[PDB]
Amino acid sequence: KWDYDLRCGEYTLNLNEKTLIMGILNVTPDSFSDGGSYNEVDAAVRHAKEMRDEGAHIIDIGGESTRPGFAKVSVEEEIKRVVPMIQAVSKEVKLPISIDTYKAEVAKQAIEAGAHIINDIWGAKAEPKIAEVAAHYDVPIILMHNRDNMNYRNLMADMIADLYDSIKIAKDAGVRDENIILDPGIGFAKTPEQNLEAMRNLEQLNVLGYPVLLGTSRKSFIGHVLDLPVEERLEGTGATVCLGIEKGCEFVRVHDVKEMSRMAKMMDAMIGK
Amino acid sequence: KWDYDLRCGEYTLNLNEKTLIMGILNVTPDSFSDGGSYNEVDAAVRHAKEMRDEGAHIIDIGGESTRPGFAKVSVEEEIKRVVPMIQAVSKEVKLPISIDTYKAEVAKQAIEAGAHIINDIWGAKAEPKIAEVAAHYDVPIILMHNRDNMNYRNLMADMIADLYDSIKIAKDAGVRDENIILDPGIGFAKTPEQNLEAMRNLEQLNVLGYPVLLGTSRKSFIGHVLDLPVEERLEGTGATVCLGIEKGCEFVRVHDVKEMSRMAKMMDAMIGK
Image (cartoon, rainbow over all chains, first blue to last red; front, side):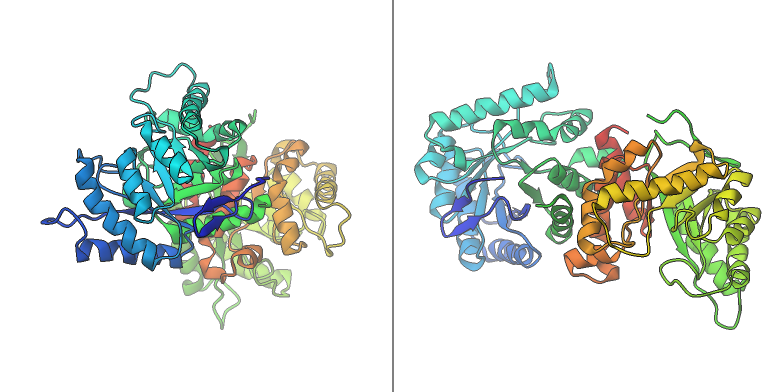
């Protein structure tokens, strides 16, 4: 299937063995500090250890500026928060770390503090220098589908075109094919019905020739279908993980590592991965 | 998709709206009685009500002779147990009832006591008169794939051939096409690796032109893949339910109605059912 492994500093991720589980770590900020506090960093570390024990292969770390909060915050603030988290987790948890940012300087500091993968919800379109950061450090970058509108002509054809535009930015900066990962940006810039249409047609992304990460965990469109609140979306998230693996996804990004890691492993066995 | 509904006495099941959820009710026999006791029947009724409240569309009722126990028991004994259960559940729970038996006389009594669907784990091969019972009463019958050996030449081609042999028995008895449902008999007469091979190739059953029920709930092969005991197979069962719906199954037979009914409903929305 894939004729290379994803190279991640001291770690290596095989793309053929198994669906790779990316566990989500959102910062719980301490009031009274701008970052690096005991309660805040220790909560991150404990959470990353639990996700490791439950089957995570990557730990995805996000500051305040990114999902789910989108706090308007300066890069200098975002770095006081994320850097301490990355330093502690990387030392204490033996797994590659992705940094969830669309900001080039936040990416550059995170990698220096120990992060191995950039995860960009804007696909190098909000800050094209992030791809130069990726190129220099020679790390994998995940380019997610996103736009500032939902005026689509043809949902899937436009997603592929938009993702191409990210690939071109990355490649023009020096990013090697082997360090490109794509993500359909489910739950971004899409109506509920479009999110479902994209799930139904996900296998089309594979024609671009890159590994695909699916990130649907606890998203609004699941609530829209099941009419359930965020804490009762486990089964709905599971359905999307399974349909994703069936349609060829190499990664899933999830909050509930124990459960989705068992679902992934069952799916892998069924489809023959 | 389907140009008829499944007719079930006062109930009607649409095959195009949604994946139909069949909730499993295994009898908990009272010691000291051969059947019809308060504790035993009331436990059945309470369970069928819970499964109704959680989203079941059919209640599947099984005596001692069938799965998971396979107790060697006379038909006259099996009827003292199952009939009281069917009478009480049908009166108290407004949903069609399937009877899980391979015995023609057990089928005939269950239907008379109120059962609407025969569910035969031997596909009319253990007792061909069950198809005559189905034909007379004009009820749906589910013909499951089974054999007394795993000497397969070509797993899937042989499954289709064997299921045909059931269809022919049913049709020769007077069973109308619209009352035939098929089931791949996952977890029967197959090695773990064959159960996974059958899951991977399930869509092949659709060429026979009948609705397909998938029944994988808590089965051994899930434990084999995940190395987990029967009570920790929810996620693994979920994976099989999702892959089944994706591959065209019209029914799933499950123990955990709440969870699998949310997974089914998410899948339906994604695939456009």
